[PDB]
Length: 249
Length: 249
Image (cartoon, rainbow over all chains, first blue to last red):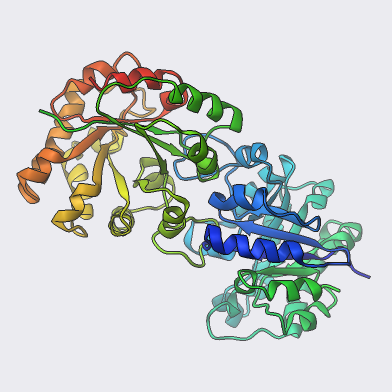
């Protein structure tokens, strides 16, 4: 029925050597019996630790970002670096970066294209803000976003890409997002891929939900056709992240 | 006289485990016999490796940037996350940050204020573009920048500040900045500290030169009354860096 689920933990701009250890021991000791890809996206600074600490065979490490070329860009970290370092997963185009870091669709397509081409598994993020949503621009918005990334990939390139649909509109505006709402957004994406690339890609594609996921609503979300996992913010710094993996079958 | 110099290595967004290892080794084995403070600004990802390896008593680790607080900033690293990790030195306001990352005078200033609170040791960056110099906007430009830093500072805080003047008008414009030219700009900044904060601070202040330096030209520059060391780009990856330290005369 569904492709391999992913359980993605987005640690953001948080952490501490002591706290992150604790969790790592917890994750490690978790028992997972089903086919699931677990991913821990940590700050660049903590990659080393998580890298040589995560014992769990169901878990890989991710970078929350990068640039495509090494060079003169003080403060930044590129793919070549990451690649040498031993990280083959990366999250790009997250709403937080889109919002405060200059990240345009044109910029996200380039990062993505760069990453894939250099070998990386990518969790390319997309989603519409409350503004776009209320003004009836959800379909124009997501299709544009996913169109832009597509414009750079070849059909074969899809094997390296995952999509995380973020309900920006419902991310800290005081709104809720129902599973029927998630589903529609996912369904859009699925559709477009199916229609513009091939049903063969579409059926293999993973579309993650990047909204507000906790231990309770994890399953009700997963229970929906086009929800192939999650990209978790808050509950990923917490033990309930384990519940989140369990909820993916 | 002059205060304690700083020979600082901004590796920017570059390196592999190998090369960094070798470089560091050379650094580890270099007998620096004078009073200088050597600094190593590596990428976030290499902070770990550098931390573990840099044995030299005269060397200190530094990060190329950060944001003030922790939280929802996908892809970003915060003053707390660095502190925890052991990093107490920071380069803030770098030219390439100002140009391609929308870090304004206010941003830079804020970060600066932040890091100083957190008990960091900051090397804050200022400089005019070629456009600006060309139109004789040097003084307005360089002073506006330093002024923005000062507004947020307490007289005491100055003890943690290190000023780095980057002749951006010289960087990759087919321009050569002469010791004479450097000194004028360093002398200007000193003028402003001395006026504004007090002669005592001015006299203690360490104003670095962040233009294109190397084994040859380093000598001459440091000779200038108001240049208290260097913020090196390219050669900070090479064995010339050694030479540059020793140009600290």
